[PDB]
Image (tube, rainbow over all chains, first blue to last red; front, side):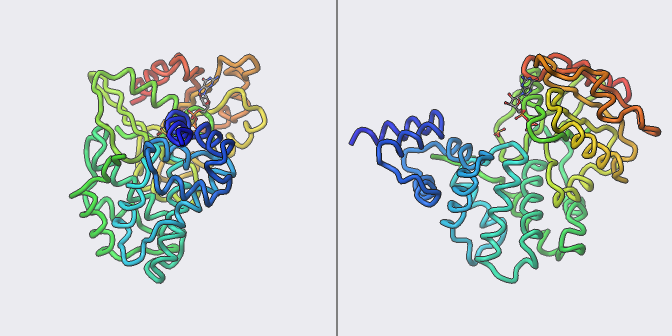
Length: 187
Length: 160
Ligand SMILES: Nc1nc2c(ncn2[C@@H]2O[C@H](COP(=O)(O)OP(=O)(O)O)[C@@H](O)[C@H]2O)c(=O)[nH]1
Ligand SMILES: O=S([O-])[O-]
């Protein structure tokens, strides 16, 4: 009925309020999994609002973030391909701690979907954060003198459980981001 | 020049960056990634990043900001429960080889709050008088109004 469309608008206006309304009106079950499924489908939802909700520090929101990541399939994708898919489903917040939690959750799922590509989830998480830093450096106009490949390779030294990642991997990621920024999501 | 801005969560880093965005005449098209703002003056520019916060990513900012000339540390002047933790985190930053030549600007933020520690109290509780080989300055601020922000950046210009 009309209540669902109202809840979506409320969500866009203030995510926690939209969720409150949908739960109170028995249109959405109050579990992390059901909220995540709602956000992943994203029907009539603003991707900035989705991202803002997924980025909140609260226990429920963190559980929703993990359940949301669980709905993504990253098998047979390289790291940048998987990040592009993930970051199309919501607008990444700018606050570093929100990005950090999102990249750690992403990395756990990436590694499960692609066993053996990275030797630890920490390596994947740190590299993913590094890729966001690269997109920022290369494509944020506030940053004047862009990072070359050599400098990006150097930025990642030591993150492979104390050692280095293959140069060819870092080159492939660098080239992909340089050629195509992470797209500003359309909803 | 690139400048790293750090501080405990909720210190006011995002709020500071948003105010700095408003002061600029150059408007910027949205990008995916970290909050970064360039403040442009005639003879100097500062590109301030919020990109720290967790230990496992410290190598990335150590490398990106290697040999950088300034560091901004933001503290919530009202958070007496976490001031010791802020001091410990500041001292970790100041022990990093990569930031050895950086001057330190401390924004003692949230001075609007009625029980906020004053500048002298923050200087004491962050251990700033203990620093030997560091040029440092404490700037009282209220990030929600913008007061103190350009004054602190002026000092940083006057060191750089
Ligand atoms: N009263 C007061 N609140 C502030 C001030 N600066 C930031 N805040 C608030 O403190 C909270 C955390 O600020 P934020 O910029 O997100 O902190 P960050 O986690 O360091 O980025 C927000 O609710 C801000 O509105 C200030 O000077 N005074
Ligand atoms: O979290 S905000 O700065 O997009």
